[PDB]
Each structure stands twice: as C-alpha cells, then as structure tokens.
Amino acid sequence: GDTIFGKIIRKEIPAKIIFEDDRCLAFHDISPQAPTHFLVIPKKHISQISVAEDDDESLLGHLMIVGKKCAADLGLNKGYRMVVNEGSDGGQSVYHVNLHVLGGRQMHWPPG
Amino acid sequence: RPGGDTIFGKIIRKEIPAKIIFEDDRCLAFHDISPQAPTHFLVIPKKHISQISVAEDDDESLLGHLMIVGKKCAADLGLNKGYRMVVNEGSDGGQSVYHVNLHVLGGRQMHWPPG
Ligand SMILES: COC(=O)[C@@H](C)NP(=O)(O)OC[C@H]1O[C@@H](n2cnc3c(N)ncnc32)[C@H](O)[C@@H]1O
Ligand SMILES: [Cl-]
Image (cartoon, rainbow over the protein chains, first blue to last red):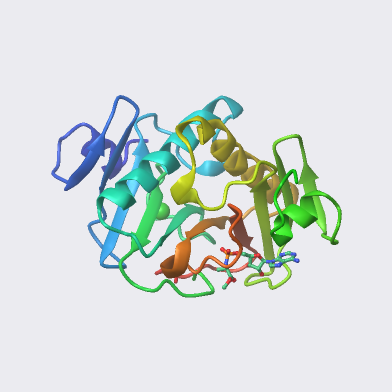
C-alpha cells in the first residue's frame, strides 16, 4: 500500500528536498535525530529491505552513493552514520525502503 | 595484498579467524567479535574500499550486494522480527576499521535514535 513517502515522491505534500534523479529522492527527515538527518529513498516502491530482489542491487547501492554525495555536500566532513531499518525489531517507521544518513554530532554505540 | 592489511583484509585471506556466515567472490559475512545485539554480523566487500565516503560510482552494484547478502543472511539466521543495517563513516560515525563494513543487528528490539 501507499505510504507518506509515496506522497513525497509525487510532490503531494512538501518536504525539504536535497537531491532528486530519475530513480531516487533525498530529503531531510521531518523528525531529525542529529543536526543533519536525511533520507534517501528509491522511487520504486520496495516496502522493506527483506523483500528487495537481486535485480535491485545497483539501485540499493545508488541510494548509498547518493547518500554519501549528499553528506559531503551538506558539510559532514567529520563523518556520519547510514542506517536501514527492517521490520518491528529494526524500528522501521515507514514501509518504503529508506536509507537514513545522520551526522553533525558524535554517533554512539550501540546504534540503538 | 588482495583485501588490504586491515584486520578485515586478514580475515578475507584466512590469516586471522572468523565465524563466517556466507562467502562469495564479492563479499564476506561474518559475526562481530563485540556483538551489540543477540545477532550481530558484518558484511564486507572483498575489494578494499576504506570507507563509504570514497566509494566510486562504479561500486554501486557491490554496495547493493552487501545489502542483499545482509538481508539474505539475516533470513537464514532466523531474524524474522527484523533487524537494523548500519554503515559508519569516519570519526562521527564511530568507524574503527577502515574497510567498508555493513553491520546487521537483530534478535532484540532496536531503539531510536540509532546512536
Ligand atoms: C568503535 O568501533 C565499533 O564498534 C564500530 C562502530 N566501528 P565500525 O568500523 O563500524 O565496525 C567495525 C566492527 O568490526 C568489529 N571487529 C573488529 N575486529 C574484529 C574481528 N577480529 N572479528 C570480527 N569483528 C571484528 C568490531 O567489533 C566493530 O563492531
Ligand atoms: Cl525506517
């Protein structure tokens, strides 16, 4: 089923967009957990990483490359953390695959 | 040397021990020595890349493969309630081994924020 991230891709509700191409969208998280906290999502509706297909490998890697490029553009020269959450135990909040990128502060261990 | 001389390069070449879950021509999945969850493993490329910030555009398929292998290993390990994947960059990310590594953590409720 559709999610709020689908609405964001479709431009039906606003988001602070950082980057877009034909296959993904990066935008600041509405509930940021670090001074910089953004998401990179595919335009293809993959509901969760556990159901991603082998043919999705380059698209998933594209999310990470876009994420690291956006992190550099946003000035995260001291580092950052990338996160993908799966399911209940993973704390996944939206059933549309989304890569979190967090920085601008020390990230701690364990990662939740 | 193929894989570099970080401890992960040593693990790739079987020069120091590891508890391996899965291995192919592109990557290796093995359990973390300091687990932060009941199940906590790493997926690393066999190609040495020091950190995600220096990955090349042509590394997209390899990076995605780490995630596909991670999710397949999580299923094979029975993490049916979910899990969290983590890649750390540099000092603020907490990176400690400069060879790209994807963490997969599960078997308990993970909390927010993720550190
Ligand atoms: C502060 O460092 C960290 O915990 C994370 C955040 N940094 P990191 O660079 O993201 O993760 C490196 C991980 O590599 C694991 N490790 C280190 N030596 C071995 C080994 N010989 N076999 C298996 N796992 C090993 C550590 O316990 C870390 O969790
Ligand atoms: Cl999420």
